[PDB]
Length: 69
Length: 197
Length: 154
Image (cartoon, rainbow over all chains, first blue to last red; front, top):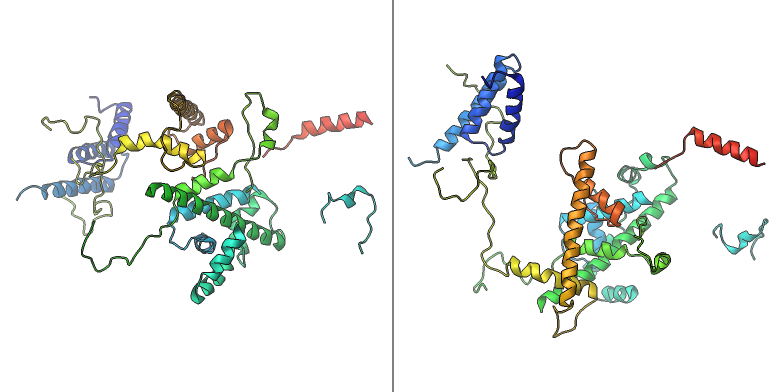
């Protein structure tokens, strides 16, 4: 329920943006979830959501490539 | 802007090395600040209502002139003409912000005077920075055998650094004690305007 | 399914850059636990070391402002009781300047500290100018009062 109030999600957005100067798979998942919630309320275009998902996918692949075969 | 004029003026004054970009930026900032900050009426003849008609630098320069080759002489002579406002009126006026601080389009004599003054400032700054750097190196002074293919022949000469320029600027800003003789014996902080060196 | 575009946007193809350690949990903890390309820490292989340079700094300044020191002597330019005073001076200066500058910056609605506030404080309270880091006129009432006074004078 904490994610339903507009003010609560606005407050959480500041924390999410604060921890994004060192992107990691989990932080990118949180950003993607935030973008999905924003889209659900007609506050964003689907194209930006797709772009966020693509960035997350690229980071995940890049991190998978660094482990042993 | 004016990086290359700065390089040429430094070369004229005794800096034969290759100073980095930070030195150029600092010197340009100093000159811009000074410029933006910037017989005779008060002669004895003016005491009356109605007038009537009438009727170590040199030594070093000479030594350097005697101690340079023909190609070095040609390069030195060609660089000696470096100027801040020689046939660059519009660019200088844009870089000096004439319109924002004064009525636009003054006479060209003012521009010539400004160029002369800027040349003098750069000359003095380089001459002092060289001494500061030399003293630092002299105090500081007191493993690869074989050889490569791109190794310099002898090296040994390095340009000046931003800290030397800053120290020289601090040294240039000091005023005479005649501007402080009226604060003797008190605890009053001295405050003044930028000094036009 | 999923919309695999015919061409990716510029944000996805980035050639990653070094990144710092953010989060606040701490670094170097030998316990149970990442960015693509973390930034290397700082290290020095061999040299004088900071513990010597920092101590020699004050003697360097004294040498600079003293004019020069002859051969066979250096370092002992300030007696033990004056070095403490100089260090106290430095600490007090730093603290006072920072305290003034932060409040001055917050006054004008800013949320970050910039060099301009420090420069303003130094210029207007200490007469210090550091290079290389980037009017008033009367109104009508004063003119009217001056005109009235001058007219009454004659």
